[PDB]
């Protein structure tokens, strides 16, 4: 599977039949149809003790990985019951500034989307959590092209060292608080992983406020490769799944 003509999102269902399931992600967020749920709590993002370890090009995106063997960087509150530990973040992005995000807002596509992936500590580890309907919480943040995001630059500058699939680099002391927007207002709905295995284990929390990144920053994302070293160059771009049917779901808003 991948994002090409012959192995892209429209093909995934053949190996991953859940691709046509009842709670697939991403979705379009119709802002007028989302309903304010006054009982939704403010989100608690507690990243002060985060321990980043490594950055990896996995052939479909790059993951910044964290130590999730203790409650160091956690997400709580909002729609969530209990404590969700940060395991990794990654992005999805386009070949052009007018596409790249997975979620859309009133059909608007952003240039990219950041996913901070967390797992519910009552399930003990990530592999068990993905087998549960409330196993994961993914915090989604839109990126638009404008001013640079200073907190992103340390990521941008290491990408040369992980150009190709399977490459990793040490990536300690990275503070993911530098990727957050000012407001934590969000939409939330039950969904899935957006890449195979497409498991229906995610509480999605998608922030309303995008972060701005510069054209130079996103250009560096687009220099990455899907291929391994010594293989024909295929630029890592358009690694996003399009919006999937909402089916029997309501998107809730934390704000009016
Ligand atoms: N929804 S998402 O944030 O883009 C997202 C999609 C897919 C994944 N997939 C993922 O972690 N795959 S994996 O590491 O190979 C893996 C690991 C363990 C299991 Cl049990 C299943 C899959 C993570 N986040
Ligand atoms: Zn993702």
Image: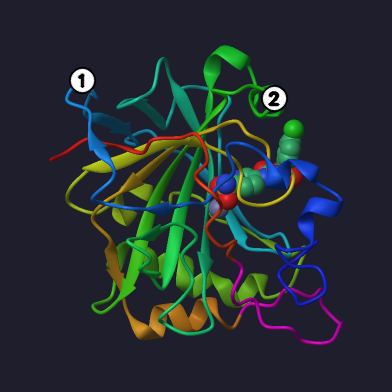
Q: In which quarter of the image is residue 160?
A: bottom right
- Dividing the image into 4 quarters, which one contains the N terminus? bottom right
Q: Mark 1 packing: few (<14 Cα in 10 Å), some, or many (20+)? A: few
Q: In this view, does 135 lie above or below 214?
A: above
Circle number at residue 131: 2
Tell me which colouring the rendered structure shows. Answer: rainbow
Assign a secondary structure to mark 1.
loop
Q: In which quarter of the image is residue 149?
A: bottom left
What's the residue at 73%, 41% (across, down)? 18
Q: Observer-nearest residue: 8 or 166?
A: 8
What's the residue at 40%, 16% (across, down)? 81
Q: Is residue 231 magenta?
A: yes
Q: Name the residue under label 1.
A: 39
Q: In this view, does 86 lie above or below 232?
A: above
- Let me know if residue 3 appears in the view: yes
Point out the stretch of residues depicted in magenta.
224-239
Whether the residue under disc 2 has CB within 8 Å of ligand 1 = yes
């Amino acid at each position: 599977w991948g994002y090409g003509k012959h192995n892209g999102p429209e093909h995934w269902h053949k190996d991953f039949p859940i691709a046509k399931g009842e709670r697939q992600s991403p979705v379009d967020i119709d802002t007028h149809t989302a309903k304010y749920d006054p009982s939704l709590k403010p989100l608690s993002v507690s990243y002060d003790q985060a321990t980043s370890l490594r950055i990896l090009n996995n052939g479909h995106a790059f993951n910044v990985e964290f130590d999730d063997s203790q409650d160091k960087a956690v997400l709580k509150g909002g729609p969530l019951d209990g404590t969700y530990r940060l395991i990794q973040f990654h992005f999805h992005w386009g070949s052009l500034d007018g596409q790249g995000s997975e979620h859309t807002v009133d059909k608007k596509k952003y240039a990219a989307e950041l996913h901070l992936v967390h797992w519910n500590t009552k399930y003990g580890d990530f592999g068990k959590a993905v087998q549960q309907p409330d196993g994961l919480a993914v915090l989604g943040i839109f990126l638009k092209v404008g001013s640079a995001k200073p907190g992103l630059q340390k990521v941008v500058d290491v990408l040369d060292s992980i150009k190709t699939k399977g490459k990793s680099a040490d990536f300690t002391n990275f503070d993911p608080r530098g990727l957050l927007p000012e407001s934590l207002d969000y939409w939330t709905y039950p969904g899935s992983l957006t890449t195979p295995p497409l498991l229906e284990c995610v509480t999605w929390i998608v922030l309303k406020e995008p972060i701005s990144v510069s054209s130079e920053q996103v250009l560096k994302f687009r220099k990455l490769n899907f291929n391994g070293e010594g293989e024909p160059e295929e630029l890592m771009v358009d690694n996003w799944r399009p919006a999937q049917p909402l089916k029997n779901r309501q998107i809730k808003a934390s704000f009016k």
